[PDB]
Amino acid sequence: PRNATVAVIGAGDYIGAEIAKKFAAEGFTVFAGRRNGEKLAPLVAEIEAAGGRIVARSLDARNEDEVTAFLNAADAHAPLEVTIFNVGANVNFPILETTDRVFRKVWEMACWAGFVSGRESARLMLAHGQGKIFFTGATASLRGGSGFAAFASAKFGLRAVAQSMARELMPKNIHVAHLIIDMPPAAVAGAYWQLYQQPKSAWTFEMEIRPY
Amino acid sequence: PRNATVAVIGAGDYIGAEIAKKFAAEGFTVFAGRRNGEKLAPLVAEIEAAGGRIVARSLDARNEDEVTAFLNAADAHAPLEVTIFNVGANVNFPILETTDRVFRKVWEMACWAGFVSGRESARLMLAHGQGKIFFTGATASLRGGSGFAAFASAKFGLRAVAQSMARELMPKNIHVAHLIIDMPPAAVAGAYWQLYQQPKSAWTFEMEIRPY
Amino acid sequence: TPRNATVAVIGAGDYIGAEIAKKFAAEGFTVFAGRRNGEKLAPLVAEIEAAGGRIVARSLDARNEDEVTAFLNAADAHAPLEVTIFNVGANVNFPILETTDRVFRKVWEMACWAGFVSGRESARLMLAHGQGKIFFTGATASLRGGSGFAAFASAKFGLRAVAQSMARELMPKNIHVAHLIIDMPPAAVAGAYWQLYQQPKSAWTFEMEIRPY
Amino acid sequence: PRNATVAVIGAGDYIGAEIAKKFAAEGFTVFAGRRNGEKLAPLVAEIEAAGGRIVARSLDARNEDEVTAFLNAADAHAPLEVTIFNVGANVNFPILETTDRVFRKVWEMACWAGFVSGRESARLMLAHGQGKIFFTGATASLRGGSGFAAFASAKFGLRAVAQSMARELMPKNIHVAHLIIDMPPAAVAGAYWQLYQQPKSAWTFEMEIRPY
């Protein structure tokens, strides 16, 4: 056991669940959040039967108050050392069929939410003097294809937040990273663990993984 | 001459004025747009003095209904052939001092507004079967520096919108372009004219200019 | 009215190169046009001269640094060298195990080495006049290396770096170094190079990508 | 042991030495090459006192015959499983001062040698049905600065070789990677160990590391 927490913002999918499993398996108390937090009960049982610690919460990440409360709670339980922001929103609409609602919603889910998760984690971590903030990217963080104006906009948006944060906070002992996924959920979790284990002398900001 | 309109969304600054001057000098009826639309009066004087046609309007680009009406007003006067989105927003705040309001407001001015201006320009131009949609970018569209989380996030976001639109609409005879600036505000207006003059067999999506 | 100036077109043997020569000659420059077999430039010379333009055709193997240097020195001696356009392609594809020592070396000599020498020697000549433009033709293989493209992409990436490094050094010294990436009509590429030529120093583009739709 | 060899081409610097020490400690038989192979004698003595296995050879990486013989020698000892190509050439000259001799020598040491190293490694590895081919890059692999025409040309060139080889060979079970440096040399060795440990479902092609 470590006297430390890991926040997994977006433990709904298999990737998010695997990240939770992995950091729990390594002795962190995992705070896991998804929209319908009752659906985390399978994951909790499995992790706790394996002897690991997890606090499951319902969380709409679009809501900045809930994100702040989620992260503050994690840090109150034990010092927050790692946040993994894992909130996707893969949608495709031709530009004319991209509504105001969809564009705003995707930004709120995939960019706005990551900004708030990143800022509030930084606030908690800088008080401890160390920490790691990891964001999940996609190929839409790198290039905007046809139909992906809403989605690529939010993912480019998140990438820029990660960059600016890294420029500011890497010199302040916070490892900001951006993992672009393009597999086993478990392989994504292993990749986050690999970023976690990097020493200060050789930190990677951006990594892309593909399955072969 | 000409029987067609140019919408210059962001005619408030020096760059926006010069673009309005340039496209009017080349025979287009320029629909200029800024916040305080009555501050366009010295520009409207100078342009009409030289024989150019200009319709000055108040415009808050964040408001999607105002943008839609602005672009519809331009098209109703003469077929809309060129939209140039040129909306500022250059701010710097450390991550912890980047407020909810700043982040959301910067996105609204610089990314959301660009998406609306773009999608609505596309609707109108596709009726005429041709047209050009140009977006002004910055170094912050390409990399996020320290303190630039809000601004870089929004410019990255605009880049992805421009990219996705280009992937879909360039095959449908609409030249979508993204002009990155690091000048003569007049030199920027010239660069846009270069992009306008390009034939369909040699269209550039992204062009970056800087002085020496 | 003739400009008292030359343009070196290194690689005037394809349609793109010929159109570049046609364009700069149409705008009043004397074009020095080089291809491996200079006698094959005879139709181009005839066409340019009948339209009122000036052109000197030479045989030039751009892998040969002595020939590149002599070609550029000759152009500058004629009239001040103002624009060099390096347009030496080489699109070839071989799986990695089938990419021979010969193919890899030759593609580098033609597409990268030749560009370095042309660039360096053009810079030497142009800096004496205090101005000039040095343009390099790139490809998508300048930006990413696909399967089978190890030799070609290596040389194109290599050319792009040379261009970047020359630009960082010489743009503040009044040389517009540029890199035009293509993937037409050939007349369109010439237009794009003319567009780059026309840019004022308050707004130069280093790299630009074009494609047809 | 691992009953396998690791070829370190460019073991004459501190980084090269550390890569050798690292893979030897993990039970590989390291084949270490540098221009004067007698200067590897201290490293051999250090690794072998620790219980590691290493063979030192003189190698001029510009010479394709020597590179091929080096890698054949490695594979003849035990299956070549990892090749790490690590031959730098960090020189700076203004363009007019970059001689024919310098531009060619730099390509020969830093690009040509890498190509031959990669092609020959792939030949040997494909016969065993697996392998990893790693290339050390620099910031000059990504952008060319003033004075770096020779170095950046060769480094860009090598990046491209790595890219093409990766596209072709990752589907055929060879992990090709490009580690961009910029720091302790042990940190570089650690990052290559990271890349070695990546499972097939989550391989990264390119990773940048820098110190903080």
Image: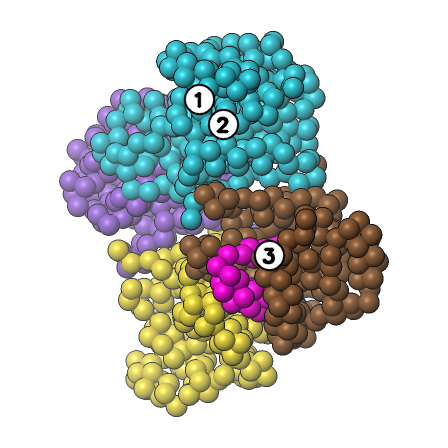
Chain colours: A purple, B cyan, C brown, D yellow
Q: Residues within 10 Å of mark 2 (few under 14, many from 20)?
A: many
Chain of the residue that carries numbered disc 3 in the rendered image = C
Q: Regarding mark 2 in the picture, which secondary structure is present there? A: helix
Q: Which residue is mark 1?
A: B11
Amino acid at circle 2: Ile
Marks 2/1 in contact by CB < 8 Å: the verdict is yes
Left or right relative to D1: residue B90:
left
- Which is the main secondary structure of the residues drawn in magenta? helix
Q: Which contiguous range is marked in magenta?
A: C112-138
Q: Is residue A47 visible?
A: no
Q: Earlier in the sequence, mark 2 or mark 1?
A: 1
The percent position of residue B210, horizontal first and vertical second, equals 44, 44
Q: Are marks 2 and 3 on the same chain?
A: no
| Residue at mark 2 | B19
Residue C74: x percent and y percent?
65, 69
Determine which residue is flagged by label 3. C83
Most foreground residue, A13 or B85: B85
Identify the chain of the residue marked 2, using the numbered disc in the image. B
Specify the farthest residue to the left. Answer: A127
- Asked if residue B73 lies in the magenta stretch, the reply is no
Mark in the foreground, 1 or 3: 3
Task: Determine the chain carrying the residue at label 1.
Answer: B
Do we see residue C101 in this rendering? yes
Where is residue C170? Give x, y as percent.
46, 58
Identified by mark 3, the residue type is Val
Residue beneath the point at 44% across and 24% down: B17
Give me the residue at 51% from left, 61% from top. C129
**Residue B114 screen position, x and y as percent:** 47, 24
Circle 3 residues within 10 Å: few <14, some 14–19, many ≥20? many
- The total number of labels drawn is 3
